[PDB]
Amino acid sequence: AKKVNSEFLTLTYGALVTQMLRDFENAEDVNKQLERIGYNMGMRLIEDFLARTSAPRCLEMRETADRIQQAFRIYLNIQPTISNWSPASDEFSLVFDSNPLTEFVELPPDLTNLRYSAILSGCIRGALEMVQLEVQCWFVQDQLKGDNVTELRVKFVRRLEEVIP
Amino acid sequence: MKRRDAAMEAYAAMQASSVAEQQANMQLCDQERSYNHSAAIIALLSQAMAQFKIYKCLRFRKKLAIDMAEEYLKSGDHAKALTLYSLMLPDYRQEKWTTIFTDVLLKTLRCALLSGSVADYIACSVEALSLRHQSDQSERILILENLWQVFQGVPPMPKTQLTPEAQALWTSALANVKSVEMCATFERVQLSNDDLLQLQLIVRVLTDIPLRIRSFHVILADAGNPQSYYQLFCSTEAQQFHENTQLRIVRLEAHMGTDQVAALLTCSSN
Amino acid sequence: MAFCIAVIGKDNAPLYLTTSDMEQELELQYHVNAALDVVEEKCLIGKGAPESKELYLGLLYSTENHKIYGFVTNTRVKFIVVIDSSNVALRENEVRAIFRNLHLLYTDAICNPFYIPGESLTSKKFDRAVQKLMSGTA
Amino acid sequence: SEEILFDCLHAEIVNYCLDSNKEHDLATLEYIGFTTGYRLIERLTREVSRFKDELETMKFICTDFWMLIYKKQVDNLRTNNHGMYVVQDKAFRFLTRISPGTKQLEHAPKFVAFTCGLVRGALSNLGINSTVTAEVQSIPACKFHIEVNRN
């Protein structure tokens, strides 16, 4: 019994999105502020993830995908199928058969533009600017939007390097 | 009940062209035609009523009561059906579940029009228009017309059912009869005998159809001393009354369209 | 055979669906069935049905060829189906399983925050899962 | 373990500090969360009787919940002369992340609000009937007094 410890985040995040909604009617506010708070979140968890894994750093793209799928595996307990590889291979698609942030919130959030993975964006984004990766993120497909399966698409841009020590 | 329905069937098979003594069988039916009063039905309902009331089972006995009223409807005996429905309808609104609430509501419409307790008729019709969105809009419009008719007292439109006798019966009515939601709020109460209150009462119509924007009324109160969205001028408070009295109106009684919502829909204060 | 799957809050009927092993109940039994279910629930609640343990109540009511089961959550939620027979081949352990799953879907919809508690179960995705439970039982 | 996700997410729960509501979170988080906790409770040692009533103290469900959630039961669990009562803990899990100096009390009640306004039951001490306020006198020592909503 009491196997699943974590079905409380799918409803904590639900409370977040509902109250952000009731505060600001705009569908994109509850996306961007939610993304920046999930960004600080990613800052806060990448430190512990590297504390356990002791990975050197994401100097390469495939190893970065491995580290990120490992991060999802350890905390959010989902297996990101790394697919859709670009010929330049600067980008890769994360295939989540089951959303880990939610467990069946519902397919209609009554209205579109309600980006339901903004923390996930922070989850993927924040760590990068902490592991020194100036990287852009965006979602190519969301099963929650009436779709079969959720794919994310994250594009590294500039190797963040420390300056003027 | 099925007895009486089968009696109706018996009349039906009688409405056919109707040798082994089937006429005596038909005479059987004639004998059976005698026990068609179905008042004994009502009495058995009464016993079941009381019997379940024995352990104080209010809901079940109440629904048998709506059964009774439905039967009086079948018998065409609108009066006591209306009586029991009159008891039930506040109850059903208290059960907050509008569906059967509305179903017995149109039952009451029939009951009151047949009876002519048009005060009760319009009370149920108006609390029905309150949240009538489960029903047809055009019938809401017709019923709103009926509302203005009865407020004028002129005969209501559902003449599609009406027949002249009960029509006159309720024409007699309303000589004696004497007397959708919005919100009341207060920007300031408990004054220093200098303040000035104003219209903080937001008059809202939840009916899709509008009610004619006729007029307004405010009623003064005496505690301690004696002293879609539509808003229009009322200047409810400009009279500089004495301090520390929160005059919260019992009921709105502004003249929108007609007199009022009368059936008990008014809020307290801020 | 027909089942009416119903969740019940304090006084209303949030979600009732009148289905059969073939399709929805074509018979004009909607209002009568709803009224019978509400009266049975109210009387049983007044008697004791409000209790801590998840309350099993088989054949707590018996209409014309429709036998009712009530279930109680400590969160004050009720659940009803009927079987269109005085006798038909089925079980009760299946009832236990199906209303356990009904609770599971209930709380998984309760996960949906846009659903404020005490409302009709609007989502056709959730409702199609419910009618999939229907197919599971009829 | 799966604790740091909730710890951080709750830190951001605090983080948005809009000047409208002392409840950064409404009781909705409560309802859904202990509804999942009730999913955990498919068995509870309460009798099956329809003719008899047996009460499941909210204290016991509170402690088992806490082991499932906060992972440290009550240290003081006092039954007030009313139907209400009070819970006192020398330390709190979210408060283990901060020193005992009284600097920002107001966060911790928002933390523990997760047990406030829980979808109730009929009988006294029946498991979930919860109206409660947080009155914390010491930083690790979190105190919470319930009030019977009825009467």
Image: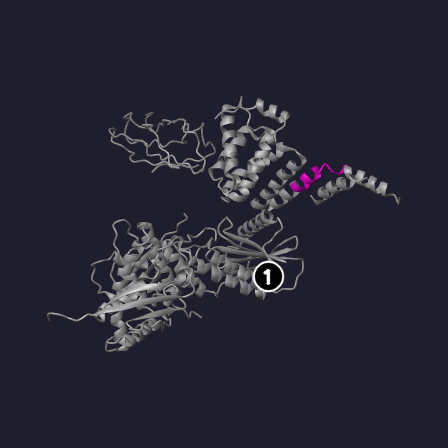
Horizontal placement of B166 versus C77: left or right? right
Residue that mark 1 sits on: C138
Q: Is residue D89 visible?
A: no
Q: Chain of mark 1?
A: C
Residue B39 lies within the magenta run: yes
- Residue C85: quadrant of the picture: bottom right
Identify which residue, C67 or B9, lies in the foreground: B9
Task: Residue type at mark 1: give it.
Answer: Ala
Q: Residue at x 35, y 34 (%)?
A: B201
Residue A45, compared with residue D110, is above or below; it is below
Give the dominant element type of the magenta stretch: helix, strand or loop: helix
- Indicate the position of residue A96 as horizontal and vertical percent values: 38, 68
- Indicate the position of residue C102 as horizontal and vertical percent values: 51, 61
Horizontal placement of C29 versus D106: left or right? right
Identify which residue, C24 or A11, lies in the foreground: C24
Q: Secondary structure beneath disc 1?
A: loop
